[PDB]
Image (cartoon, helix red, strand yellow):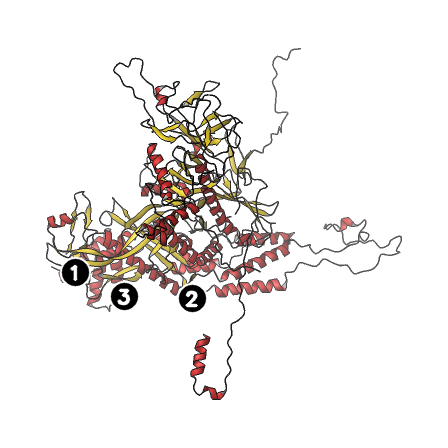
Amino acid sequence: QLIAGEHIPIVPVFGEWGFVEDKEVYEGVVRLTKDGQRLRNMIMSFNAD
Amino acid sequence: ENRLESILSRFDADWTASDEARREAKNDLFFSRVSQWDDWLSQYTTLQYRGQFDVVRPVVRKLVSEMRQNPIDVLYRPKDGARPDAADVLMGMYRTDMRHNTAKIAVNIAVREQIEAGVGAWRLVTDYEDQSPTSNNQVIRREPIHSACSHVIWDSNSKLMDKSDARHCTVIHSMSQNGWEDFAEKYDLDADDIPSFQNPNDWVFPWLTQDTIQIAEFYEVVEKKETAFIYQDPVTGEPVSYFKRDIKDVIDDLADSGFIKIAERQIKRRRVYKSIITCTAVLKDKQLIAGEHIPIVPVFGEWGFVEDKEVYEGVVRLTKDGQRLRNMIMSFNADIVARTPKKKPFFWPEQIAGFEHMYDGNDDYPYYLLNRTDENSGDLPTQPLAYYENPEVPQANAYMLEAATSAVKEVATLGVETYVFQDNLATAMRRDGEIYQSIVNDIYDVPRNVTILMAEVVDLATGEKQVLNDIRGRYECYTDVGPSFQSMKQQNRAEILELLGKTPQGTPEYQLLLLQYFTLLDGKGVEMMRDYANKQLIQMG
Amino acid sequence: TLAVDEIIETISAITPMAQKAKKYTPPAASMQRSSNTIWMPVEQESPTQEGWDLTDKATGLLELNVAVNMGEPDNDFFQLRADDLRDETAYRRRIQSAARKLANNVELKVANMAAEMGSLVITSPDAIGTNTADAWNFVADAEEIMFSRELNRDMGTSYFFNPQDYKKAGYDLTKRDIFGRIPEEAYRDGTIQRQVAGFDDVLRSPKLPVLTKSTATGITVSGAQSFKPVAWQLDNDGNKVNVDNRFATVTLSATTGMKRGDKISFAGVKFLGQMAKNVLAQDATFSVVRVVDGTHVEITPKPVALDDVSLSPEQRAYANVNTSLADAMAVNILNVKDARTNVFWADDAIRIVSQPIPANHELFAGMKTTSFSIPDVGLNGIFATQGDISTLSGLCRIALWYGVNATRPEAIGVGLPGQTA
Amino acid sequence: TTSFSIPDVGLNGIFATQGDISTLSGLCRIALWYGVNATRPEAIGVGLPGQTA
Amino acid sequence: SPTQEGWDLTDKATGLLELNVAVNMGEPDNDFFQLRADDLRDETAYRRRIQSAA
């Protein structure tokens, strides 16, 4: 079914975007903080115990 | 004697020469993009905790934003002794075909790779556009080269930052199956024969590998003296000269249209040839492409030669060690926190025999009770109660974590500011402007501005194809670096505003204000204002 | 003590036959169901009759075919112990050496297949250095037999020497006591010429096989046999199964001493000019393909006799031998002494069928697979890594699937110098 | 493993997949983990026709 | 690298093996020369001895 226009009508929006080894990578602001957040949650749970 | 063998010999020599720098740059890219635990061995082994507490990424983000907030683009300025407005047409063409998203995205990619690994690059290509062409039914566009450190290989005998003296360069294209099919359709190749070339990643990080198809493009620059024809223009003039290679299917058409051959000179110039190759055979042999320079523009960070060996560096290579040590220390300390027996008392079983339910943790009792006597020992031996010691993070761990964090913070300081990186980017933009000017001279219809209006002299062959006619008086403007503007109207507006910012409030201030009103966009109110400004300027003469 | 990253290069191999062999990649989806075999037609030959009245003499149509298939993958399975210093020091170069070895194996299979299926045999009772210009004589004999048999050579020809015979040819050229251009080329460089006696490519191949002598003797045909060119035949259920045209099983007195690759020629059978059906002066030479049973052999050029009465005219139009076996003719073995082989062919006679190993599919999750590009030879395989936690190790495997086929065994040839005693 | 929606019935399951490098083969497993419970047997009924002696 | 043919290669994986060679330096090639103070009033013999040594 032919649709109007000359392009795919989907517009993407990216954060930190790049290629590593022919492989696309994107990142926001949450990926790096996850390890520290998970450690802090674990430590607080242990201390509550 | 074999062309394929010669090309492969050059490529192998260049690959082996650049092996070290490519490996270090790829390591830096993987460290700063995928993960900071780059071993690939301790994944099949026993599993332990490995945390990633990043301290280098904020520096890279700040540097990327800082160097990006000041865009840089080519600016053509007339030479000495040339006409004052000799760069207007070329500048308009550049802003026309470099305003698209592809150019900005390629520049941003190159800048980010220059910050992280130390080297980036982009490419300039020419295509046939039939809808909105820049000139001569053709457009010039800029495309990115991802992982340039491993994908673009320059001539090993090059001692310039912009690689302007490099005689050849090989670019390794990696594409999916559909990408290869599209490439074969585009370049009239056979889609059944999958191309075969060296893997750019060179079999590192096998845990990070993708099913890709590799082909190579070999650009070579040949400088030679070639015959140029001197004609006499029907509309005045005399030094109108053309190259015999370009005027080869319209030689009789020139005479028929009114050009009489005066003389003939041998003039030295460069030709760029492209070859599409695999590791076994050449697909396209020496397809001549437009331009005097290899269409790949490289950007470097901290670049130099150590012992005839090219070394480029960014901002992550030095901080890698401290960051790794900090990660290891934090992982060790998390293991100390997690897997360690807690602080509980040491009891003999007969000390609490019968009173065990008092020590489970409930609060139902006002105190605790202990057994006193044994039927054989008379009384339970007296000894102070011991408690398992609380977990402690060692002073060595704490001190070395502090030292590693301080070392990374100290060594991850680009410059004092990114002035050197921006200067290298400006150098790359100067090379890009040179390449673009040559390509424009080779494919576009550049009018000649006479002081007697712009004159465009072209003729059509018998096969209906049109051949451009560009005189040898072509290099009338040189390349500088200025702010990035999307159009000539915006550039004029910026220049007028800059002049108005320093002009004292006299008659030139009024003149510049009226000019700024003249050069405005159109709605309704700004249309009325521009009409008023035009009338005022015309009346003032 | 550790090393200093300065590899000492010791091996430099070349793959001329492999790089000059044509490579074919049929559709994988169809090949999987067709069981890794595809049939290709052969050039059609028509009969011809003379006369005015030709009632009930109208012939039919007969088109023959051959089949090309594949063998088994050539792998480089190797393990990687985690707790060893070499784990990252050597695995990359192991990958590179695997690529080189795979290319070499492809070349070896090509050379062996050509030398064992080469029907045309040129034998010399003395070495290449005996007389003067006898190397050119050896090449010109192959050119003349391929010209007299009316074999198609549009794509091109090739003649691969073994290094000893190539050196003998160069020595014969240089001992001419004269120096024009060819002798000076052969003196400075070892080459004789790129083109000799009509061949458009005369190379030296370092890994041509040595055809060991056959001890077979006193072998005679057991019973008159006639071979008919057909394209299909009925099976037990009544299905029409195709027939490969490049094979004929003959019954002999005893196949003692025979082996795959032996060159034979029966007594009285002479070649034919294929198109013109004119009797040549050279004995029909065949190459045994496989020794099945104990009294049967399988020779690749099917001996379709011209004087066979039991042949339909269309079948007789495909004749390549002037007579048929007669239960008494003796078979002479042409290779009577050990000698490295020089192999000549037409460039379209040998092909390399290839198929991909689709290990990139989602079915292979947990194993990382990429495409591997073999140098020199134009082939692609897969490179797969998986991790085993029972042994705390990482398995690596470079797989590559292909098969070497000889579509026209009558076009391939073998040269045997010193075939005395 | 990935999710695998079963049509008709409104259920999901696990589509798991593994590969082998020794033998170049692989395995798939469509697992559907569910349990039927009759929480009101006094509300469930059964109709038996033709239950003559 | 060794290679094996076939589809099923379970319990047939090989290890990695590397060889290496040693390069070193032998004894020096000296040249002694003793002279008194009075023999350095011409310097031609000394300079020619240096050249011959090289």
The residues tagged by marks 3 and 1 sit, at their Cα atoms, a distance apart of 20 Å
* Earlier-in-chain disc, 1 versus 2: 2
Residue marked by disc 1: B537
Q: Secondary structure at mark 2?
A: loop
Residue B448 % position (x, y): 17, 56
Image: C415 above or below C63 = below
Q: Which mark is residue B415?
A: 2
Looking at the rendered structure, the secondary structure element under dot 1 is helix
Q: Please, what is the three-letter code of the amino acid marked with disc 3?
A: Gly
Residue C90: x, y in percent?
Answer: 53, 53
Disc on the earlier residue, 3 or 2: 2
Q: Which numbered mark, 3 or 2, is in the foreground of this view?
A: 2
Q: What x and y, as percent, mark residue C134?
A: 37, 43
Q: Nearer the viewer, residue B322 or B249?
A: B249
Q: Name the quadrant containing residue A5.
A: top left
- Image location (x, y in percent) of residue B329: 58, 59
